[PDB]
Amino acid sequence: SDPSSINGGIVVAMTGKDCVAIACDLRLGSQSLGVSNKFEKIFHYGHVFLGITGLATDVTTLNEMFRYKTNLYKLKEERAIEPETFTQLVSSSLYERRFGPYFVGPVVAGINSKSGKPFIAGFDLIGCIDEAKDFIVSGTASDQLFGMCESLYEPNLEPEDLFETISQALLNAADRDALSGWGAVVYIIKKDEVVKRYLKMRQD
Amino acid sequence: TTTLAFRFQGGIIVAVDSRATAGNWVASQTVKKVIEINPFLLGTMAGGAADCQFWETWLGSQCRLHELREKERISVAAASKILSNLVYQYKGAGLSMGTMICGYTRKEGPTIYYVDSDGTRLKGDIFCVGSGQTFAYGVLDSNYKWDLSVEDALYLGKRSILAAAHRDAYSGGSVNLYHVTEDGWIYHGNHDVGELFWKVKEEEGSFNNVIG
Amino acid sequence: MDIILGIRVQDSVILASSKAVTRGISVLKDSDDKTRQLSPHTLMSFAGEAGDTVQFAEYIQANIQLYSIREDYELSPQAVSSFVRQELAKSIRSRRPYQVNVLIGGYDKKKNKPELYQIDYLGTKVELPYGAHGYSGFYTFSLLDHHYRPDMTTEEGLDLLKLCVQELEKRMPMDFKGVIVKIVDKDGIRQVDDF
Amino acid sequence: MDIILGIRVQDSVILASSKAVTRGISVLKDSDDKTRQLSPHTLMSFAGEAGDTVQFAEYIQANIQLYSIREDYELSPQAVSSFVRQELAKSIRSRRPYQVNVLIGGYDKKKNKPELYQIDYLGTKVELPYGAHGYSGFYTFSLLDHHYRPDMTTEEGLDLLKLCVQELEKRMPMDFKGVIVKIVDKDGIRQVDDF
Amino acid sequence: QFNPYGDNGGTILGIAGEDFAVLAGDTRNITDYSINSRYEPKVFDCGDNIVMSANGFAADGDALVKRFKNSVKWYHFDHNDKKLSINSAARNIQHLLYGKRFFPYYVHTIIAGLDEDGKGAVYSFDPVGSYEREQCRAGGAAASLIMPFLDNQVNFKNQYEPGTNGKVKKPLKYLSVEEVIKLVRDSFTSATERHIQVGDGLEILIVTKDGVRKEFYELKRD
Amino acid sequence: GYDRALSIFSPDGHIFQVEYALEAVKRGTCAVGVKGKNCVVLGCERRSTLKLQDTRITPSKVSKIDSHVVLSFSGLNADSRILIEKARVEAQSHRLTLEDPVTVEYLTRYVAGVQQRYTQSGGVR
Amino acid sequence: TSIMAVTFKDGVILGADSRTTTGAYIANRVTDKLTRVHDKIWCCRSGSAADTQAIADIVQYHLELYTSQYGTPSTETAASVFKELCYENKDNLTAGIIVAGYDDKNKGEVYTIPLGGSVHKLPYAIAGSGSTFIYGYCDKNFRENMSKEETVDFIKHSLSQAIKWDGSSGGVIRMVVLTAAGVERLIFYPDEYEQL
Amino acid sequence: TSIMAVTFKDGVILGADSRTTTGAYIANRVTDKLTRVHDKIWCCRSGSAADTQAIADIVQYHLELYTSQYGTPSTETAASVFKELCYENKDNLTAGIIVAGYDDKNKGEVYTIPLGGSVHKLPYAIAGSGSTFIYGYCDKNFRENMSKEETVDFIKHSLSQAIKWDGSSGGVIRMVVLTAAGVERLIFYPDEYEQL
Amino acid sequence: TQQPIVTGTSVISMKYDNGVIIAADNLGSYGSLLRFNGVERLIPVGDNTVVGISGDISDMQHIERLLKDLVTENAYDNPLADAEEALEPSYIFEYLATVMYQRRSKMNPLWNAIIVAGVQSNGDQFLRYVNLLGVTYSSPTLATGFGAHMANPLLRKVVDRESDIPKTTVQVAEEAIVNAMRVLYYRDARSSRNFSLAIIDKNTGLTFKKNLQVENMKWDFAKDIKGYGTQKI
Amino acid sequence: TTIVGVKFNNGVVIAADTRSTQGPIVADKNCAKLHRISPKIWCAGAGTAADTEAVTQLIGSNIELHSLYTSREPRVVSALQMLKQHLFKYQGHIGAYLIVAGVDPTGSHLFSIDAHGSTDVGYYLSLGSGSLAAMAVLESHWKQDLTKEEAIKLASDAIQAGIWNDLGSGSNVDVCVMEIGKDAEYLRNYLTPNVREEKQKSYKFPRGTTAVLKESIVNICD
Ligand SMILES: [Mg+2]
Ligand SMILES: [Mg+2]
Ligand SMILES: [Mg+2]
Ligand SMILES: [Mg+2]
């Protein structure tokens, strides 16, 4: 009965040369019992990508909530929300539930369409923004992801190389966690093309 | 853990997984959960790794002392009862063990005993033990017949561990197979779930829940 | 309460739900129907806390029926499942949450496809080829992982379901007094009387 | 463990004991014999804490068998029951007490009479026409209060026992996988194979 | 109430090659948020080409190493100076640990050396004596950070041969001592970045048929 | 506790207390064992200087250790009861742990071990 | 905390140590526990730093609004406002406050308000953890109608002893003199008071 | 309890109140907390009545057996025996004892033994619940090499204040004078000491 | 299982080029009551070792007696008791460390943190820590309690690693220790102004300084601090 | 966290480390603990990260509105009053421990605020888990009449004490100088004494190493 480790799951984001990558596993379980191997944890609102780990009901709820809020943003602003602005919206929304929080570990990833700059950010369950040049990690295998990223990562990787690095970071981290894995998805994001790849990984 | 053992026309199949965990941390994927006591006796391990490992290798020493003193291999019944009586002495102290003592003797034939740390000792044809036992039962019970061939029985034991390895978060790694005959136990290999799952999925057509 | 199962095949969704209602050391009833028809092509089964289960089920039923009358239209299984999820997601942070787990089996008439949704009391929704709530899953999931194929007929699905009930009747500690089986397809909802 | 019953009729004592051994959410065995023959005309059934039950039963068995060999004589059912009671009465104030409840069915060859003793883990002994341990008594005692007569035959006792098992199979929450039935009379102990 | 256990932090790591084995560990010792020592070694040469570390609660760690060292001494006294093989050491350590099953040594134990065929050997123990031989093991505070990296770079897990459609795995091969030390150093600098109880210094003990050699490297002191 | 070493070696290498125990056996009533093709028969002498005996209740010379093994003896009658009791207890203990009655060789080996122990323990004859 | 307030011939003097702690760590060694709620009505604070500050701030606001409407408030009135806050919020407060002021009609006055929120008008008051150690000394040495110099010495010697024995107390001895002449702040350092 | 022992020119004097309680009920108002463990080695008892009595009885036995073999024991030796009992049985004791004796070589000596069973040799010692209130007073008023009359007055005034503030203390003030001249018992009643 | 009653606070120490310095104040606290002021918490063993002890004082006095007995026992049948077979700092430590860990293992600890400072027979500096848990460690600077949090950072600025030790004189080292003692008096609520300091040098031997006082303190700035925010007078 | 504040001749300087932790794990190696309330009033914050940020933003927002309303430059005592009353109201549940400093028409100021709402005044202050290491340095080297460059040196030295000695603190030193009559100068990463050394190896994988099941283009346009 620890809300952040009932369902399991992980998300990781990385920056490369004029690109960003965000990846997640596919598992949804109930403690020991694996239930679903199709549960994707990455969503997008326009060109801004959001990954969410933690309690699955809150993952779903927050996706629906940020779709709601970004849709109204676009109608009033007459433009797509940028990663920096969306990051602030996520932080505000989470801190609004300061003393009754969503049990989540969200991760923002995307490229600012005006400046062309790659942007990633992480949050704790109550809104503290954790910005990074290199990588953000989240989920039940966050220790493992920290270890994988901190050793495997190097700056200014090309999209095809960045794919290999982030995939190997996720896969090997997931395999040391009982609650993570059961499939994986990687998003490679360039200024105006996004490629989504499903990874072959061990299914235990 | 997941472990299992059953009896059929052609002896005993014994299969286990190979994962060790500390909470949600996957500690090992290569643990030996079958212990070879003698050429005719096997022991399976589930629960506390040290508890099982320590006391089952101790059991092996007691079995060796029996055959030195009695000039005859120990019965599966007497071997299992040494272990059960030992853990019963420690009852309440916090030992955690779910074990199966499998073997063949002339007087008994193929025999399986379930022995656990609260002192339960049961003779039976089929048992599944560990956190993934239910998943193994689901597949094993729904495909079990006494008249299975040695080839089919080996696969079913392997397939039942795979089933549990896939669904139980605390099971996995690889499958270790054993076949026990009138001539003793025979090892039938280590089978990594990493390759075995996809091979079974493709050839069998099962595991449609998984993204192919 | 206790055992609720669901299997989605080629052309239908089949729900099996245990008939026992046990309180203390007494089985009070052995013919309990743990299901409500939300709309002509949508059925919901439920298990969980006593009182909460039926109260929630009938509350959802009333809301979907109200919608049906207002718009002269049947909500899609996906739409109904999302409404149900949100109600449970609200509930989990209430003063007293609904402790109810549900399966929703529906036939989408616009898509001509069967759909099965598993939703727990927290509001955790997943679409599945086969689903279970409680301890049942610990036996049935692995069994279905082996024997299930996505192109099965309703008859094949029923045989696959018989295999699940047999396993549960062999290895489960409690006597759940068999199951009521219902099929959801293009022609609506019907009950299998001889199971 | 769980269900152990006993009925003393005109010429015999009949013991019925459930066959299930359940641990967690798994029925590990459905053919378990929860009984030990203490002497040719004395049978003891047992239920309670895992491990403790068989350990106690076999310990008593060894002691009675030792007595039999020493004196070349069979202890009376009354004498055996008193020995068993004292062992449990000792046990209850030990560092770790035996959590085992027993029924002892015996035929006294000197008296030519069947005898049934009910002894709980505290060492509470009573001689009874019919006995039960655990939740079973809550259904069977009232049933037997109505249908039992002191002059019944072994066949009548078996039908009376069928009535008990049927009631338990209807109203008990758990699946106890039927019973093994044994008869103790002037000719010793035998097992009914078709129940 | 008196709590007989403490946590002294730090992390350790053992890798085995074809004809060598390394056992590394950081030299930082901590309690709570304070540093007790920047250089307190916890990897030891125990004789007979066996190196050992018992990481976790240092008082238990030191007690165990002390007892095992003494066990090696008496093994010689009782069995005509016979060399204690790594497999025999492992089994002996299990009994040392399990002997305190109901009041455990609060440590993750790793030993390294060469087996009786001259090949590199690493054995790892849980706090109550469950043991297993492996090519690879990290222990202690940052084990969860380092171990997955070792799975990937030592055992080539999740790495397939390019262009083979994820059908042919990257083949297993022994690493050179130069390659192994690179992985150790990168493992510990990565751990030092993200774990507060890891830093100050890194001491590696390398075991070949010629004996036990040491190497020291500075780690970040923050 | 009484500690005296009563069974000790003499200059010629004999243990006189053991050898004198054999003289007690030589004084005892004759006992014979003969085994056939499908049976063993134990025969025992009973001295007839004792008339007015009650043979219903007088200890029999052949004792059942278990339902399948018997023990007869020659020598001190009181001593034999101690050996028979220990044997009978071991018989039940064996059935309890091994789940099989003793072999005749095992039961004999146990009884002989008890006898040996009383030849190099302090304070006992 | 060791705090006290003492009436004398010309008015009243307040005294305090300067130690604020969290366990055995001294978070502030130069604290000012003598607080102005009005020109010539001050208080000594003990207990929770946060609670006593919040109370003193509210009281100062109340007396400022009182003065705007009804002119200078009496010391009794100031003590009543402190009491009202301490009594009605007794479940959520850890505040031991001594109120001291100078009227021209009433001269020097001291009111002590313990944990419960009761009020006690006294010739002098001692409070805080360190007060326990000087009950004997203060009772033996206090006289009514002392001079300014005598009262300063009485407080200095008293708080010196309170500081010596109480680990929670220490630093400097601050004092505030309230007379017709005005308001005087005094400070005394360890090197003076320790060797008394 | 409020207890104390004070060394002076001619030897040492012990002092105590006479109150024994169970909660707020005074079970005995005329208790004798000054206990002989040897002719000229006495102790003041505080804490559990049962514990301190049992300890004093054992010590008196030990010193009687010591005297039989080795002659008169030193005050230090008596304190060591008290310590040994208090230290080794610290988990099961609530005893605060002050040991005081007169040698001809060493003159007056005072040893205090708090809860843990540590030993502290001092010029004077105060202990018991009432001691807290006179730390200030006693530190300010104690001088070394006082006369008998001065030391009696010091203890009388000190315990008077301890009694005044501590509810657990009261009744009469008992004192025992230990000098070369012998052993003198003094008693002082409320009507004298209350109005000091 | 215990609870400490009369307690001593920080013990601080460091290595310098020729030996070691160790210091501890003279206070025996009784909870928040600063009860005893003449307590010596540094105990010399021979002329080459000083043992500094914090924590429970009854247990400290027990350890004193143990060390005193160790000196007596070592002299027995030992013609070289004041020469080659004199007690080394390393022997004294290992003995205490053994006792401390044995007592924690019997769930009845000596409630102390102990620092053994001395010079070995070969001239080497010895400085090692042991506590109620039996935890041992060594460092160029060692401190217990608040000293660990406040003294160590100051002493590490002088000797930050092994190579800094030869570069540090006894004058510089003592100055750092004395400053650290002042800082502890500012900030530790169970510290006293009076303390003892010991120097064990490989040339000049054991120098034991009693009745030292914290001095050159800054308090004047306190006069300028009024109120807690907005108050002006 | 370690955070400090030091007053000098003609103003005040505050500094902080840049480590953010979640248990023993370093979550953020370069986080900004110096917060702008108004142009010339800045806050250093320790405690719960989201709390220090949120409470600093809210009061900063209200201070801006107040400044616009009153046509006056905001005062440090106003930010102090607003922060303390907000924190007191929440009875410590908002875990913000703040050092508030700045210059205004009244002069230069330095305060600290506890999570429960109590406030301090001083010439030098430190808060956070590394405050004892920092305060040790401040108590050793502080004096009356510090210059600007002396105060920066003292402040950053006090932060360094925390970086090296407190496991809760690490990485870099941020500084903000608020001088009377001048613009406040925020010095982000004023010191960076914890740069990661070169890695021993590049872990760039051969392209094709990762096994892939599916590919698809994601539509981000309308
Ligand atoms: Mg698995
Ligand atoms: Mg640090
Ligand atoms: Mg007591
Ligand atoms: Mg009184």
Image (cartoon, coloured by chain):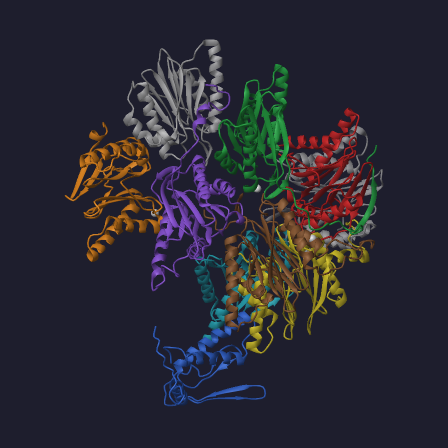
Chain colours: A red, B yellow, D cyan, E brown, F blue, H orange, I purple, J green
Residue at the image point whose x is 44% and y is 81% from the top: F116
**Near-viewer residue (H3 or I78):** I78
Q: Is residue B191 above or below residue E149?
A: below
Q: Is residue E194 above or below residue J135?
A: below
**Near-viewer residue (B184 or E154):** E154
**Near-viewer residue (B8 or I107):** I107
Using the rendered view, name the quadrant where residue I120 is placed. bottom left
Q: Residue furthest left?
A: H181
Res. I4 in view: yes
**Near-viewer residue (H32 or D166):** H32
x and y, in percent, of residue E185 in the image: 65, 52
x and y, in percent, of residue D120 in the image: 49, 57
Res. D104 in view: no
Q: Is residue I75 left or right of residue A14?
A: left
x and y, in percent, of residue I219 in the image: 43, 29
| Numbered disc total | 0
Indicate the quadrant containing the N terminus of chain A: top left, top right, bottom left or bottom right.
top right
Q: Is residue E171 left or right of residue I138?
A: right
x and y, in percent, of residue H127 in the image: 30, 39
